[PDB]
Every structure is written in C-alpha cells, then in structure tokens.
Length: 295
Ligand SMILES: Cc1cc2nc3c(=O)[nH]c(=O)nc-3n(C[C@H](O)[C@H](O)[C@H](O)COP(=O)(O)OP(=O)(O)OC[C@H]3O[C@@H](n4cnc5c(N)ncnc54)[C@H](O)[C@@H]3O)c2cc1C
Ligand SMILES: NC(=O)c1ccc[n+]([C@@H]2O[C@H](COP(=O)([O-])OP(=O)(O)OC[C@H]3O[C@@H](n4cnc5c(N)ncnc54)[C@H](OP(=O)(O)O)[C@@H]3O)[C@@H](O)[C@H]2O)c1
Image (cartoon, rainbow, N blue to C red; front, side, top):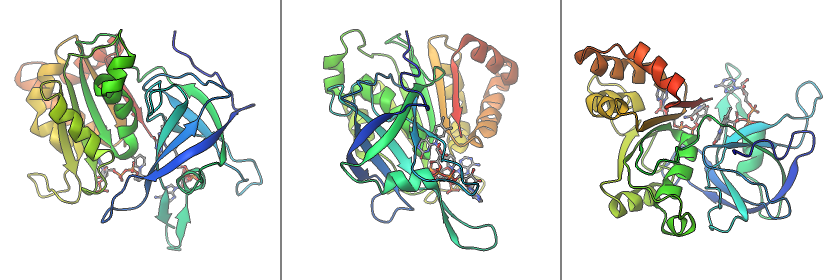
C-alpha cells in the first residue's frame, strides 16, 4: 500500500525547518538548497519517488492565497538521518529576467524556501505520486535520466540502494542489480550531491554507473551544449540493451525537453536491430517500466 495524501491542502501539516544547506559550490550558477524538515508530531509517512506540497505565505497578483507548489522528496522514507524523523527537499531558486522589462523576477515558493530559516514553520502536504516508484525487485536494472533538481527522486532511490545505514535499516531490500544515472547540470559546481554520488560509485562499482552531462564545460560532437540526450545517444546501444530486459526500469525526471532527444537516440539504436522505438516504448509504458516526471 502506497501512502498518498496523508495531509491535504485544506489542512496542511506544519513542519519546522531543521537545516537549509547550499548545494551549488562556488563558481556555480544560482542557488540550489537541501532543506531538511522535522516530521515528528505528524509522523508523515512517505516512500521514494513521491512528492510533497509546500504552500508558501502571501497572496498573488489577484489577491488570492498562494497555492501549493510540488517538490520531489529528496530523502528516503527514513529521512537523511535514518530515523523516520525528517523529510528533505532539493530546491532550485527560481529567478529570471523579466521578458523585456529585464528586471530580475523571483519565484514565490522557491525563493521562500531557499531563504528559509532553521526553526521556521512550513505548511507541508502529501505525499503524492505513484508513478515514480522503484520496483521491489533487488536485481532490477534502473536507468535514471535526470536534469538539475530532477536528481531528487534519484537520490531517494540511490540512497535506499547503497547507503550503509539504509541497507542496515531495510532487510527486505538489499540491491544487487544495476543502476545507471545520467545526470545533467550546467557546471561542475552545480553537480548536486556530487561527492556522495561518487562515493556510491567507488563503493559499489559493478552496481552503479554515473555519467555526467555538464552543459557548460562540454560540447556534444556537433559543437552544441552537452545535454542528457547527447549522453543517451552516445551510449544509445548500451542503454537500449538494458531497456530490452523486462527487469529494467527507466526514470526520467526534470526538463520535458530531454525526452524527444532521448527518443531520437534510442529510436536509432532500436532501428539498427529492426525495432521501432515509439511502439516499443508504448508497451514499456503500459507495462509500467517507463517512469516520467517532468515539470
Ligand atoms: C511533480 C513536480 C516536482 C517538482 N519537483 C521539484 C524539485 O524537486 N525541485 C524544484 O526546485 N522544483 C520542483 N518542481 C517545481 C516547483 O513546483 C515550482 O514550480 C518551482 O520551485 C517554481 O515555483 P515558485 O513558487 O518559485 O515560482 P512561481 O512563483 O510560480 O513562478 C513561476 C511562474 O513564473 C513565470 N515564469 C517562469 N519562468 C519564466 C521565464 N523564463 N520567463 C517568463 N516568465 C517565467 C511563469 O508564469 C511560471 O509559471 C516540481 C514541480 C512538479 C510539478
Ligand atoms: N532541469 C529541470 O529540472 C528544470 C525543470 C523546470 C524548469 N527548469 C528551468 O531551469 C532552471 C534551473 O532549474 P534546475 O536546477 O532544475 O536545472 P539546471 O541546474 O538549470 O540544470 C538544467 C540543465 O538542463 C540543461 N538543458 C537546457 N535545455 C535543455 C534541453 N532542451 N534538453 C536537455 N537539457 C537541457 C541546461 O543546460 P544550459 O542551462 O546549460 O542550457 C542545464 O544544464 C529552473 O529554475 C527553470 O527556469 C529546469
């Protein structure tokens, strides 16, 4: 049974911020924060791949109360401390330049969160989501295609799979399959969780493969910016070789734009072997092995 909607927008849980820590190291673009909340007092229950709602303070350009924004849960069911006391979020600060006034414009909810203080209280809803759940099979192959903060569900998967204290805490799940993360960010300092993602890979080298698409330090073979789909095309045949296995699940989280190029890269690899990828993918979706969360 997957717990969904334990708290509803009509009556959110009031969490309290435990810590708000930076994820973009110096030299990096913008602000992405790891925010840990205290759950105790509601005992909000959740699993990996799900989202929560955050309702920020304030009203909009129309006088209306701000509605919730969804954020992917970045911690496992146990929280980062492995004690079932916390839930963590991975939040990029949304700011752009207004479309010809040119004034810096701030996103309401994300700017509230990335500047939120330890001890502050936040309205939390959920969890929601049943489409981004890991299979129970510990020998499953798990392809993880992520841009930016799309890393968030991938951290809940990879932590449950490979953190020492998670294995200790999950006797029913001792992962021994193969996981492959293709992770796209703009710079090397924008690789969220880089150190831990690389600890995992040296710790479990035959179980986790880690591939970077660093937008602004790497050009694809045709002189453009190196995106996730350029990595997919580069390893298109390796990927399609795993996707052909019925033990294999694919998770795509982040920009909706990564998709059509992922579909181009795999459609070519599929074609070489006589398969047409748009039908094959239609069947992977119906089977529930093609998991997509883009926003
Ligand atoms: C299922 C799901 C999961 C998500 N997970 C995460 C996550 O893990 N981390 C995360 O950071 N976010 C995540 N998001 C996005 C998050 O929900 C918010 O949309 C985001 O943080 C921005 O909200 P805000 O309140 O900061 O911005 P808002 O105040 O709502 O402002 C957004 C609005 O700004 C305007 N706008 C935006 N960009 C531009 C532009 N370039 N030019 C002109 N106008 C523009 C648009 O009208 C837009 O709809 C997720 C979204 C969903 C749906
Ligand atoms: N990535 C996401 O999950 C996402 C989701 C929704 C909105 N956005 C927009 O991007 C901002 C950054 O958020 P973030 O931290 O999540 O992401 P981020 O740190 O910007 O990482 C996103 C990466 O995706 C790359 N990218 C850009 N266009 C792409 C495309 N068409 N196909 C594949 N990859 C592409 C970007 O490359 P260049 O920047 O170097 O082009 C960047 O390297 C958001 O605040 C919002 O304005 C991003």
